[PDB]
Amino acid sequence: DDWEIPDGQITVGQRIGSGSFGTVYKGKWHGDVAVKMLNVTAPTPQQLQAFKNEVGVLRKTRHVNILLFMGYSTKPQLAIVTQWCEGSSLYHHLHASEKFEMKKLIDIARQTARGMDYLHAKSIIHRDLKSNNIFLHEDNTVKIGDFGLATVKSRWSFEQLSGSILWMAPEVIRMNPYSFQSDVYAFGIVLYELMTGQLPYSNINNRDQIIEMVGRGSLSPDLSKVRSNCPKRMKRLMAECLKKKRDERPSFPRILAEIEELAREL
Ligand SMILES: CCCS(=O)(=O)Nc1ccc(F)c(C(=O)c2c[nH]c3ncc(Cl)cc23)c1F
Image 1 (tube, rainbow, N blue to C red):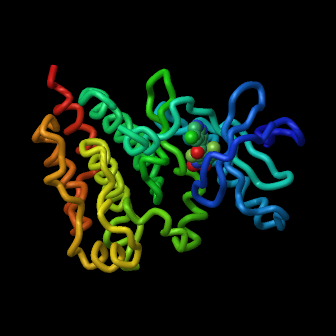
Image 2 (image 1 turned 90 degrees about the vertical axis):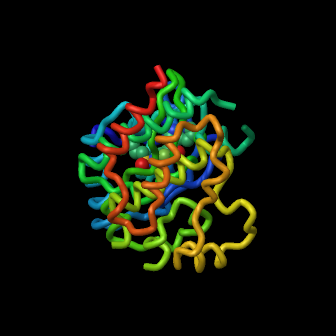
């Protein structure tokens, strides 16, 4: 409520990309900020109460490895204001184009697992984990985005599957469906991206082919492409996260404990 940034305080600039329910912009309001412009303009009584409940959730769910909520807007569009992360997204680094030392590669995974251990402990299902939602704030601390509006994601379904699907668990394709284990699968794809510097199924230039094959469980990421310097324990953890049978996947407590243990390596 006292989190509503008043009319004409944020200077909306450079279009960054598009998160869950909105479009991200680089803004300015007492320094650098990020603004997610939601696709809602004239909020009805129910719409405005729904959005204010998620803002109440946003100001109650704080963590060093999840994006920092700064406030909201109602005019001219419903928007979410967060902290700005100067080092952009992990996708931007890894894929566009190449390099990080094995220590750092393990450190991002570790910090993503730390944030996700916090989100799962607050009974929040992320629904949309990907490298484009993992931001490098520097202080050199990973920041998880798109975790908010979780109840709105549950109340709806999503069709905005493309352009994504790469981090979607097989059960999420063949439409339970979203769980903590589906979040573990997306994290497994993140681990793949980290240890391989490539996206899964980068040879395919078609969507419905990936939907049929990943969904039926005939396709999966090519693990043979893992770096030679990737420790054994990490290639194994990655496989456990990516397991087709959803209830075989590890929990974030066990995920984090494996990363902590394999980080030594002194
Ligand atoms: C505390 C709520 C976070 S969120 O779940 O609603 N997701 C969200 C909301 C608003 C945003 F601007 C962003 C976002 O993408 C960024 C926040 N800070 C950033 N810094 C750099 C880049 Cl490239 C992107 C962002 C974002 F991920």
